[PDB]
Image 1 (cartoon, helix red, strand yellow):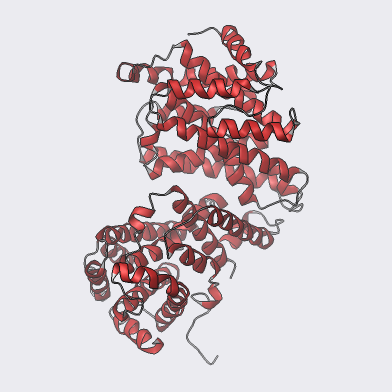
Image 2 (cartoon, chains in turn blue, orange):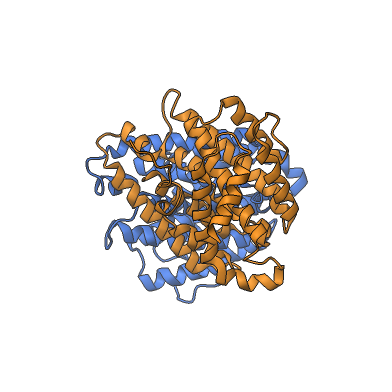
Length: 270
Length: 276
């Protein structure tokens, strides 16, 4: 229910406590975040009586947008070198362990992680979010290494890393943390873990078509019709996802949520 | 001892239509390789489980399962038996009951042995599960080289991970030597490496089908180079994880043993001599 610009202002307010944070980070966060929240709104309405978490709770909504902003900011920090390597390392340790940053200029890290901890419906989801953050950080730095001071790895390594760097796992975990979506339990299902990997691969492939899959393959296998291959790969991952989602029915709002992510395009938020 | 094991696998194989001597030889050869590589490791779990590494009964059973898997693959790919017979066989093996059609008594005998010898019976049910999964992957991959438009490399590899049967191998090992895979598969890192080792096995087998799949869809693509890079890549990822995780013995050695083992030591280069 919170209005778009007020949400941006709330995200920006917190964002100023992070060196390198830009207005763009807050805007993208709210745009991507609203896209998702709007598509799972009908479902969240149905789980609300049970959980006690309101789909329109401003506190939950802005916290979610702040996590998205943090992820956008980190990606830029990593790729555009907005802060020093020492600072990025200190920031990633803090966000990955859930402790305050040891270097100054990044107070927002401790503040957001504390709110998430405090607001967690099922605290297992908070520990998972810290795990996903460490995976995200590792992937951003490994991907960044590849594009330059490297000797390109295999498409396999590329995709495995890109699945972590696309951060869909993080987004899902944060939503589960805030609205009590029981992701920690759902993960016990193999079909669930597999769809997580699939929607993440779908997102990584789509983003790169629109470390990058095309650039990597073309400069490693120039004769190879790279772009054709990838679209095929993307359609393949999509068929597998459709299959698994059919074979198994996940509790609400998971169906709508995965659907929303497959349909989302970097273009609608970036 | 080699030849006595080979003959015990062979003898049982006479109760499976289409079984060839090579199925038994490939089985013992690959199986011997795995068991001798993990031996020093299996000695430490030995007193704890009471399952002796040199146990002849556990050895012959393990090899028969490998032979079953090789035979099943050939039946699917070469049509050694009818589609009707293949369905009845896969049905039986997936439920651990005798095959309903004549000529396949071996199915009953092997599944009864596995049920009788299972350290942790949860591994027996899991083996049946893996057998159904393997059969389903065999079905899919055969029906794919014969339909309309083809599979993506991702779909092929995903199916290929199930069709290489490494899950079945690990499970059978746990079942006979009580390696507690039933609780280990609950570990996300253990699941991740099983997938990596299976992708490695599928690519290795295929580099001696992925190649044909890719060359028929992308003629200008240096396919064999790409697949070789993929194999190297999965191998590096396997090493990265291994280095960052500790798995109860003998799992580390077992995983490494399966990673290395090159098909040229087993199933892809064993056949009956002919004069020509």
